[PDB]
Amino acid sequence: GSEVPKYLKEPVVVGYVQRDSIAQKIGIKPGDKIIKINGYEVRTWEDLRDALIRLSLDGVKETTLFLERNGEVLHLTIKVPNVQKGEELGIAPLVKPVVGGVKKGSPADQVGIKPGDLILEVNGKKINTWYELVEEVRKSQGKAIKLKILRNGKMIEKELIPAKDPKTGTYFIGLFPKTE
Image (tube, rainbow, N blue to C red; front, side):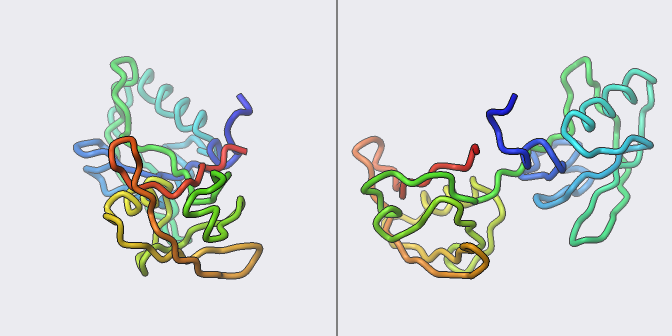
């Protein structure tokens, strides 16, 4: 389907690693870009899926996962998962903190944030996933938060205050993820 941005199909980039997962056991990290597995090239998530299935069918028990971390290539040894039993690697796709839309009136519509902005840092701690953004907006507990952002080629800074909600008293700021 076309209802997701291209980067969520290719290349394959880990956003989260699950506890007790195969991926966790072997030290895969958010940021890693899976490029090959065994002798199958992994350009897209379907490539990864197919690769894992094929190996699992051939009854192959272990193989080499190739990934790129910090522009350099690591080789890792993996247990081929039980595909038919729905056993997975344990990786979720990365959704970057590029802003897709802003809600009229929100602490982020106020403080100037625009669609297309990329959020590289909040309170001097670097981030690379959307859930890390939200994760900090939540834990913020009222006390406003600094965002280091990349707009149109330049860094900028915005400092905004999380609005507590008449829902569950949870702090939001009013940014939608980019689905375009």
